Image (spheres, rainbow, N blue to C red):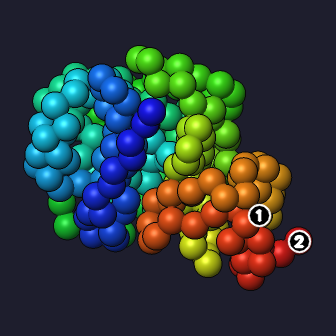
Amino acid sequence: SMRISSLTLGLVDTNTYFIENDKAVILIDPSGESEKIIKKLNQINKPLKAILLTHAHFDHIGAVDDIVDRFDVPVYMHEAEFDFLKDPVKNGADKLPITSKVTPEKLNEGSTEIEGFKFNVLHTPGHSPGSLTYVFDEFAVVGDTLFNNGIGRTDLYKGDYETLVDSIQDKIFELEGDLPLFPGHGPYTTVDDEQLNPFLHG
Ligand SMILES: [Zn+2]
Ligand SMILES: [Zn+2]
């Protein structure tokens, strides 16, 4: 019923995801290289209805403004990182040309329906305070939380190691053991495959 596609883009190889149903598409983490994203959006030939952000670090939002300027769609994210968009010290870009001037819509933990797309939102902070995981019937998009044999870094702004470990162990590890998990970087993994992840402790 849904098809998930991806491009790996930008300075730090961010996974941008395209979620299609029979009649529309939503985009998650438009990281950069917006002409490549737009090219695939034009290939899909279904109207883009929304952008979802797992979080608002610079490498997940670099193409947000270009896509909104072209298609005029809402951008959804957790309110705890609204101030990340315009603030390069908070989103990490301060460290050559990244900000977003969009006014975002807030999303909270719970069941959601956006333009015919039904999914569950989990608030999974620790790598960032507004990190969200988006759970669909046949896959989940987890952001910079649980990687294949790795974990999101917890030394960024408002990051915290024990918070992320709890988010992974108490929320992401409640999903179906073989559900494909698609993180912000690197290949997919699953809850079963990450049971002995060595970065989780406590
Ligand atoms: Zn990040
Ligand atoms: Zn990232």
Q: Which mark is residue 89?
A: none
Element class at badge 2: loop
- Report x, y in % for residue 54: 50, 46
* Three-letter amino acid code of the residue under disc 1: Val
Quarter occupied by the C terminus:
bottom right
* Res 17 seen here: yes
Mark 2 surroundings within 10 Å by alpha-carbon count, few (fewer than 14), some (14 through 19), many (20 or more): few
68 horizontally vs 193: left or right: left
174 horizontally vs 68: left or right: right
64 horizontally vs 33: left or right: right
Residue at left 55%, top 48%? 139
Residue at left 66%, top 58%? 178
Considering every residue shown, the one lying at the far front of the view is 1
- Residue pointed to by mark 2: 202
- Report x, y in % for residue 96: 20, 67
The residue lying toward the viewer, choosing from 173 and 154, is 173
Element class at badge 1: helix
The residue lying toward the viewer, choosing from 150 and 22, is 22
Q: Quadrant of residue 115 in the image?
A: top left
- Report x, y in % for residue 49: 32, 24
Residue at left 45%, top 71%? 186
Residue at left 63%, top 32%? 120
The residue lying toward the viewer, choosing from 5 and 86, is 5
- Residue pointed to by mark 1: 165
Is 68 rendered above or below residue 189? above
The residue lying toward the viewer, choosing from 42 and 171, is 42
* Res 158 seen here: no
- Report x, y in % for residue 31: 31, 53
* Three-letter amino acid code of the residue under disc 2: Gly
Q: Are marks 2 and 1 in contact (CB under 8 Å)?
A: yes
